[PDB]
Image (tube, rainbow, N blue to C red; front, side, top):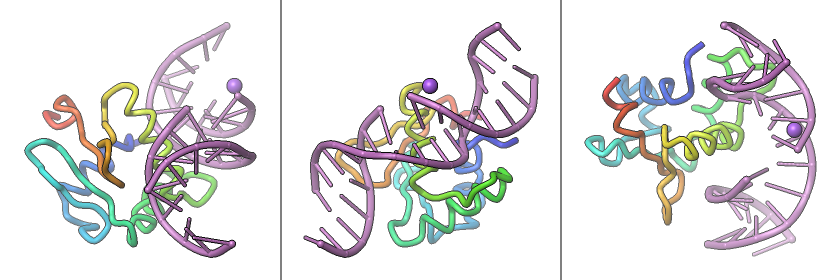
Length: 92
DNA sequence: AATAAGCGAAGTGGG
DNA sequence: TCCCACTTCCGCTTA
Ligand code: NA
């Protein structure tokens, strides 16, 4: 099964949900979710995973928090809904 | 208050 | 056995 960071990177590369997520500085790997349209993207994540319950942005962000300990994805301080892929994730 | 967002122990998958 | 990679639940804090 695809991992959450790869799901998000693939969305950013494809442009398929441009109203829900976008690059802020692609060279740095920084991206941001839409306040108003993030739930649609969270829903897609849960459907792609085949999870039992409906996925919410809150649950998806709880998973993202675990990446922050390992550095896979860092949450940008002093910003909302903004994150940054590690250099390793971006190299493929 | 209402709403949004940040923060951070037990249950489920698939090894 | 016991870790992976989240998922779900619960609830407090900050804006
Ligand atoms: Na526990």
